[PDB]
Length: 137
Ligand SMILES: *C/C=C(C)/C=C/C=C(C)/C=C/C1=C(C)CCCC1(C)C
Image 1 (cartoon, rainbow, N blue to C red):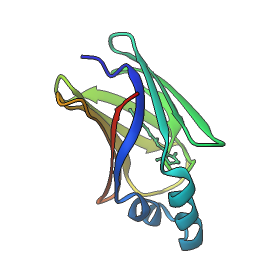
Image 2: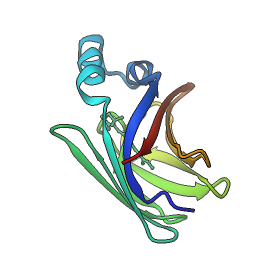
Image 3: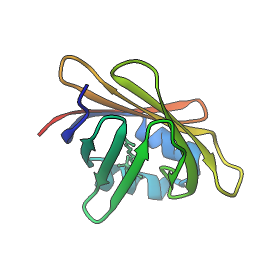
């Protein structure tokens, strides 16, 4: 299908509980939530190759990967990891992450397209699941 587009967020669930699990402490969480949980996402897709830009007001992250091809990126909390993306359906990809150094919670994210226009992100830390919902620009 086509994940390609400029996405803006309409819903966000359990983002604070995600950071709590990740170890961010209370004060930092509250701010992070309030300032930096209206992010912009841009995706350009060339088949099974992905460019992904996620940006706050003063921060940007650029992710590049081919599906099935192991790459390096960051956990939600800024820690470096090895990632691998696989398909689970036509409109849904899944990514597992292994830390580069450290022990830490088990992290992953998924990404799905509805047919009703929605782009759905999940990020997972152990048994907590943050769900963010986007529609197009
Ligand atoms: C396919 C979609 C992907 C890979 C989206 C990833 C989104 C993130 C890794 C979001 C990360 C965030 C931070 C690292 C801090 C600011 C808050 C978020 C949720 C925008």
